[PDB]
Image (cartoon, rainbow, N blue to C red):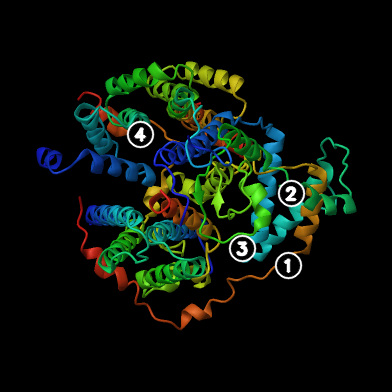
Amino acid sequence: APSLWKGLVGIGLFALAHAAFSAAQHRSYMRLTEKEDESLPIDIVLQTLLAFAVTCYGIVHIAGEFKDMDATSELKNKTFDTLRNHPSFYVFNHRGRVLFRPS
Amino acid sequence: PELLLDSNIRLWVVLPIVIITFFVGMIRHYVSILLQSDKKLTQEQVSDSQVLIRSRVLRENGKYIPKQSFLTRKYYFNNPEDGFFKKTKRKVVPPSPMTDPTMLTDMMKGNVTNVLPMILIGGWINMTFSGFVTTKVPFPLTLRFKPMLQQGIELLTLDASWVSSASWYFLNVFGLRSIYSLILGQDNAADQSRMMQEQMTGAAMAMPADTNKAFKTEWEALELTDHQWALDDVEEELMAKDLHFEGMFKKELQTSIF
Amino acid sequence: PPFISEAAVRGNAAVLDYCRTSVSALSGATAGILGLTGLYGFIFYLLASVLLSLLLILKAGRRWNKYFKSRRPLFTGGLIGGLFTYVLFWTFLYGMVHVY
Amino acid sequence: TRVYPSKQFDVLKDDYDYVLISSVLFGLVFATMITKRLAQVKLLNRAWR
Amino acid sequence: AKVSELYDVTWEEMRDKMRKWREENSRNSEQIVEVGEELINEYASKLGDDIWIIYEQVMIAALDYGRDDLALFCLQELRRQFPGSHRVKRLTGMRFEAMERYDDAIQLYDRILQEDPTNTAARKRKIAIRKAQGKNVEAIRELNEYLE
């Protein structure tokens, strides 16, 4: 699912860049002709807005973490058996060591 | 829209300046990380810190604790006969902050003089390009900003919208201020403006400037605080319902054993 | 609500600010591509921020009480610095295309 | 001929050495890549030691 | 199931599972070494920073399980890059304690304390050496000393 969102964001960005290039070409043409104070075509403007709205949808989905506020829920599954052992104090005196010693 | 510009001045000024400021900020952040050095911590100061943390934790979490043990803790801390904080005294350094002077210093120090290094960069950049027109800002501006904005073009009829490279880079500095943290994280130290200003989480949180005075302050703070056993209210759970233990018990079947 | 974890709150705030800055950055590019006046541009920026906030609320929907204690930061948050970074990318592509 | 009213404010300045600019532009990237590994090894050494 | 398990995994999931095991600090030395040496021979390409913690974890598990050969194999790799590192010294002292001659391990801990005054791990390991060597009363006294 994240890969699809990333690809969609990339495609939208590419479409936005293409719309920018089209608008640049339109203004370059406009500078050629005297007067003619007209606006850019509405179709490419709508394409620009479509590319802007699509890229803002995946930009929120890509980073969604929203962790739980309460601090009791993560330790709701953890068992006291694992907590009983600690990594500081480890005594290396067990029957498994002499049982696994030959093999 | 007027003043038709060349296509060679945009590819040789805008992009270079943008990359220059980007990499300057990144280099500053990396060098700030590199130059960071650890501070020596002595065992007595460490123990003082841990005792302070213990007393502060007692102050914060004191409701969920037996009253007898709470009074035993508080007596051990206070103990009018011997007293741990009363007897244990280390060296004292003569102070200098004063009430009115420090009350004023809170504002006098501030961060007023932290803009000059960026002004130096802007001055060098403007020195490189004497007569140049980078871009125009759509925002209307007043003619009293033109001397600061242009600073090198001899034009009095021209509007102040057309900016020079100096203000262009100046606005470029704060444009990526919130963008730098996007790639790095919440704790970002790539701010080009605050170069000399040290911005970090801070090595060795605990700063016992006067150990004895802090001891006495905590001694009186622990005497002030009361005791209210928050455990004594157990009847609220008494009349209730147990349905969450039915809750993931349904969702605890679905996982098997690896 | 009695006990709150600072790590989760920090992560939530960081995510919120990250989306706020990214949406603002793209809003700047759109306005620079089109090209408008200051009043219309600022109004457009405000509209984009409002749309982002509405989508952010829609993202949570139910069980939002556990996620966010309140909604004030969701509505009013990063409005000035986001505008500071939006103004840069607005004029970045504005004069690059039109003036140049 | 062509007459210049007030010097020039529309054309790129003639004396604009590109060697210095290109050298600085490449050196910034080179120094960033140099300092990246230094920071990584500093962090690793501090963590281990 | 061994081949079946090794088939339907990827190195990313295996590394993430090892990280989760580290987070839950469980006692599964058999499975830790089973997935430890497997990724050291299959991937052995990148993730140095992760694989150093993996080396230490695998050797810790092998000290528990049955295998000192892999413990020394990871010890030489750890010593290759960082010549002076107190963590490797602590690990070597723990393995020495596990084998024989506890006194030289105690001497190594004493030297480590002489170099770095603030070393909680070495003191904890000495406290554990006297938990199993002598009575628990002396170990209790020394644990109280360090805690104080």
Residue C48's disc is none
Q: CA distance from mark 2 to mark 1?
A: 38 Å
The residue pinned by badge 2 equals B110
The residue pinned by badge 4 equals E50
The quadrant where residue A68 appears:
bottom left
Q: Is residue E119 visible?
A: yes
Quick check: do tags 4 and 3 share a chain? no
Quick check: do tags 2 and 1 share a chain? yes
Disc 4 is attached to a residue of which chain? E
Q: CA distance from mark 3 to mark 2?
A: 43 Å
Q: Which amino acid is tagged 2? A: Gly
Q: Are marks 4 and 2 in contact (CB under 8 Å)?
A: no
Q: Which amino acid is tagged 1? A: Asp
**Point 52% across, 80% down: residue:** B235
Residue D44 rendering spot, x and y as whole percentages:
46, 29
Please tell me whether mark 1 sits on a helix, a strand or a loop.
Answer: loop
| Left or right of residue E10: residue A53 | right
Residue B32 rendering spot, x and y as whole percentages:
57, 34
**Point 22% across, 38% down: residue:** E11
**If you read the primary sequence from the N terminus, does the residue marked by circle 2 or circle 1 appear first?**
2
The residue pinned by badge 1 equals B226
Q: Are marks 1 and 4 in contact (CB under 8 Å)?
A: no
